[PDB]
């Protein structure tokens, strides 16, 4: 049990602020167009970073150490709920966090400032590889980068690429980040159209002998895959909060259809009653896992296993809820116009984002063994 | 068990003929374009009705009484397998059959001839209603039709609409079919874009006081909903054969990826091994249900329950196979380019076509009671 | 997320006290014998009510109004975990609570005192009917009871039966409770041996014209089905806490087998890894639902829907975990000796106790509609 | 589709003969007692081998080469259906077949004769090992056997043990079978009580330096694990036919309860209607897989994959049907008296017998790869 009652006043006010923003901009007509444009207007994105977050650290580190993850989760779940869509916000929050972790204050200052002044980021994160094999090597007097990055959000048009690479230019192979201008010769972007999550266009980006300057390398407090890997767990919480939100939007449509429509009403049908309770059980479980993992961080008691179990369960559960919602709306609602069919497609995509189910099993099983040995 | 071995030589030759046709036309490049055009070229459709069906009654009644349903199923399953797509063929076969049942030979002769000469039908079937309330009534010296038909395949552009209606023009409400020219005033078509099955574009069609002539009414051997309802069961067999075929195509891609790719090979992974066996079990079951229901008809021993159990199981099973195939292909393959993601969308649509799962439960449970009382 | 860290110190000490008691008495050898005797020894039951509950209201109302339900849940989950069995404790707690609700202090005082002095209750609750039709009627100068009660825990040997009945002895049919001595003529008990939950033997009890005295009727603050129905929701929380505990015991055996045994170790098997994570996800969800529903009560913010969703999910989830544990232990462990096979049987029984899944759907769907209208 | 219509007259007559035998002996009262005695009376077992099998090779090789497997399947499915129990017959049929394969005619003649004259076998098959490590070695002038066999049907009391072992007495480790008298010193049997399948009592048998004579070694046409492994696939078909039969018995009780009882009738309940159709779909699939695998053998076109897919699907499906039947019968029927709860327990056991689900995945995945490469 974790619903409105049970949040603090401060947390509830945050929701109020986010809900007033979402309702204002995320109309069905607006969202339909923005899905088509694969992106949000300057005004909408700027209004998001201008939001009154009620003192929570949502786009800044309130406590000067970490963000407030539960707060971030409430923001993402609510915007995903109102919009019924995959929004760019969670991807910005993670990219911001990752940049801060690996680069000096002087290096990140320009980018943070741009984000606060426009609500957009001038760089795109490029980490995943097809199968890590992206290298930087010295030829003579030059540093040259070779590799291929996959699933690069906004890879096609981003002004710059924040690229993870093995640096080999040292005497006798280490983890490294490079902020590479998209204008450097040898960078090729190949847009990948996915069946869902239209507003988060990705690309495959190939680096073919790209000259990189030393000043481009991130010189930060954090180092190594270890640090990156921790940061990507936040990405899983974000993704699950989005899945929960969208799933919740599908459930609202199902319920509204069920009471409204008649076939006496469709909601007095045993089949529909069970589907409804089945869906509310899944939503309850999703929310409990997402909120629990998030509140652990904020206590300073994060466990890897919580995040792994959450990621294993929620996107698949979200997809099943959205699918059940389609079944309740009947033949219409397999129509592209209906947001439930977009939601269903979005949620299916969450089963690939930020590590698959199969990867969560590999991460979780030793932690489970460890947990039962330890008790 | 029902695979190649186990078919007669005649049945196997039929497959050979269909497979040679499919391979010839249904290239990935061709299918991609035809998905985009929402329809097949004249040459391809004409080549289908020109096919050597090895003496089976596929587009004609070989035995002069019925079509050869198992043969039709092999044709539809194979074309769906090769194409990885929802093809128009099964919808033509049913529309042809339904026309013959309800109209005189003189009435159907022009339409059959056009189909044999071009591979296309000049009419579209309009039966489903939103919730039957489509009426024909007399005003004075005129017959006037009012109603709304839903999910009308090619409703938007078809030259004529074969419409099911309550005729009230008799003295003291009966089932009736009307072949209405699309040019009759008061006909409004509203295209419905679905998330899958692009080549089978549907429309909502409203009839607003449309003047219908007496010569348009179908005067046939068959009469009443009873007859129509029987015919629509064939439509369920067709739809399930399509689901099986497409599902089978998804499985082939999964297997080819699994052996080819490596992550040593991806097919030596316990997770993938189980998914594979799980998928082959579902395909085995689907095929057994579809082939069994079809062979029952051809024996003259059709049972309603067979068709209901088949329709309950297969589209959902097909969707799960296609989804498992996506999961095996990984992140790519949630990409629109990959046919597995279209297949997944197609198969989800089969859960609405020709009666839902929930409708099959309502049909099947009394037949089950009857079956266990009877033994 | 709700595990040891996250409980207060007070809650943790309670667990320590309960765990020291459980470990002391509930040995495999002891439990095996007690399963066989279908009951616990006087010493064990007395030690339970003598337990230091760390000031929580577990067998008494600390706050003078209600019990402390979350505390009760921790007690029941832990004893079920250590024992791997269905224990009588939760059934006593509910029977105690129900007695207090419907009877005067003078009426309940003897029974409470006996329970505190011996750890046993001298009465058995008789409410469920086969399908409410148990009546009390006046003949002449007598009051006569007729009806049949089902699933009466310890119905066969309990000294007295607390019976729910329609009283018709008033002038112009109302809810009523009667504390009937088992020695009253016309009471017939029929023991029902179940496949699981051996220590909670039930009976069908028929009342055939039993003379009941007026002094036997419960004269309490609480009245009507409404009040009874609320009390039975506590019974659902108790039952789910037991299911969670037993399921948790099955998981521990699975994990211990997996690491210990080898087939290199059985836990490095992809199949086992996934089963393990799947099980830990279900346990996480169960615990979240049970703890959440319990903490709601203690806040004074109980919602019927929480208890309905919990009861819908947990016993079936518990059965699946226990079954997965059996599959991991292999062929042995379908052996009666192995506690995992008893646990599996116990948990299957929880799907009938305190209202079925199907009854939870009927309860939950209107509350869900209400919840989404209200927001 | 594979039901009564669809069998030949000969096959149908066989069923009639088996059904008349089953109905005659397998009364609920008789079965209840025989479950308690863990075995069938001499009269019942003798009547089985005296059955008129209508010329099929059920306990003999009609064609002089193989048994008639489909016929055997009909016999086992029908007896399991009528009895609602796990019967010894299928275990005898396999043991008979295995003996014939590995031993000379002179060696098997006494055992076949005893079986035909009494309906019982004087030996018990001992093959499975805990983890193959059972050896025969020479000490000086003696041959000595050491090993431990698991899950030995009737291991505790069988007059003789047919034991699989590595023979090392040759100069420079080979597969071998030994018919060992239970009276040989050093044989220890440990009865294992399982939660289901009472009539098929198993034991762990330890061989501690047992002197074996050379005349005890089976000298047969068939040799090696390869041959044994093929024979054990028949055991999987038998086990699945038993699972199907018992599952079918559970379904009949569910249906009879549903129409008979009322809660207007319980069968007009949407929840029950769906459970019913879900169950009949699973039974349809089970029967199709079992009958298909069996008919393949009889055609001489056995594929390993058919048997693997069948074994993967059917016992788990059978358990789900039996469980759904329990849920429909309600609270009673978790009672030991009700045969549905025994059936449920039996079917759960089939998930371990003759190779687990997890073992079928390992067997099936390469055959699937092979199958899709081959086409």
Image (cartoon, coloured by chain):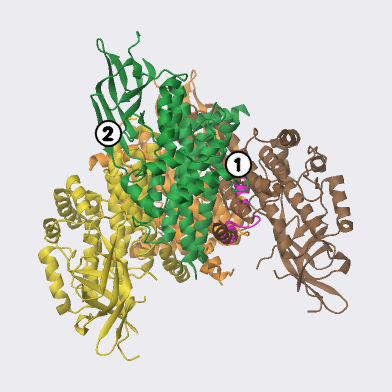
Chain colours: A yellow, B green, C orange, D brown
Q: Quadrant of residue D232?
A: bottom right
Q: Residue at x 10, y 65 (%)?
A: A117
Q: Nearer the viewer, residue A299 or A42?
A: A42
Chain containing mark 1: B
Could you say which is closer to the camera, residue A369 or residue D6?
D6
Give the class, few, some or many, for how many residues have Cα within 10 Å of label 2's Cα (few <14, many ≥20).
few
Q: Is residue A21 visible?
A: yes
Residue at left offset 39%, top offset 66%: A305
- Tell whether B216 sits left or right of D364: left
Q: What is the x, y in percent for residue A226?
A: 33, 76
Label 2 resides on the chain identified as A
Quadrant where the image shows the N terminus of chain D: top right
**Total numbered circles:** 2
Q: What residue sits right under mark 1 in the picture?
A: B10
Magenta residues span: D335-362
Label for residue A260? 2
């Amino acid at each position: 049990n974790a619903m409105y009652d049970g949040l603090s006043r401060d947390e509830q006010r945050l929701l109020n602020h986010v809900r007033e923003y979402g309702e204002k901009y995320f109309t069905p007509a607006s969202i339909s167009k923005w899905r088509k444009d694969q992106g949000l207007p300057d005004e909408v994105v700027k209004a998001f970073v201008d939001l009154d977050f009620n003192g929570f650290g949502v786009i800044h580190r309130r406590n000067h150490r970490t963000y407030d993850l539960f707060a971030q989760v409430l923001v993402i779940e609510e915007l995903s709920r109102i919009s019924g869509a995959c929004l760019p916000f969670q991807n910005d929050l993670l990219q911001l966090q990752i940049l801060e972790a690996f680069a000096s204050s002087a290096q990140t200052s320009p980018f943070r400032t741009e984000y606060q002044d426009t609500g957009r980021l001038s760089y795109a994160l490029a980490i995943s590889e097809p199968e890590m094999r992206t290298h930087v090597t010295r030829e003579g007097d030059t540093l040259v980068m070779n590799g291929t990055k996959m699933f690069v959000n906004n890879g096609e048009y981003a002004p710059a690429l924040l690229v993870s690479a093995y640096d080999k230019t040292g005497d006798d192979p280490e983890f490294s980040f490079w902020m590479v201008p998209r204008s450097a010769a040898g960078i090729y972007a190949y847009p990948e159209q996915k069946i869902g999550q239209s507003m988060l266009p990705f690309a495959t980006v190939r680096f073919d002998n790209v000259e990189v300057k030393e000043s481009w390398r991130l010189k930060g407090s954090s180092k190594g895959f270890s640090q990156l890997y921790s940061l990507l767990e936040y990405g899983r919480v974000f993704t699950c909060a989005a899945a929960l939100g969208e799933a919740q939007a599908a459930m609202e449509d199902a319920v509204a259809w069920a009471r409204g429509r008649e076939a006496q009403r469709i909601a007095d049908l045993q089949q529909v009653q069970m589907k409804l309770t089945e869906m509310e059980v899944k939503l309850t479980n999703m929310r409990n896992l997402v909120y629990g993992a998030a509140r652990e961080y904020d206590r300073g008691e994060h466990k890897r296993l919580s995040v792994a179990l959450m990621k294993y369960y929620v996107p698949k559960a979200a997809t099943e809820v959205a699918s059940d919602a389609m079944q309740i709306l009947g033949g219409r609602g397999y129509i592209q116009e209906n947001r439930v069919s977009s939601i269903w497609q979005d949620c299916r995509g969450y089963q690939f984002a930020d590590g698959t189910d199969e990867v969560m099993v590999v991460i979780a099983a030793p932690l489970i063994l460890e947990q039962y040995k330890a008790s």
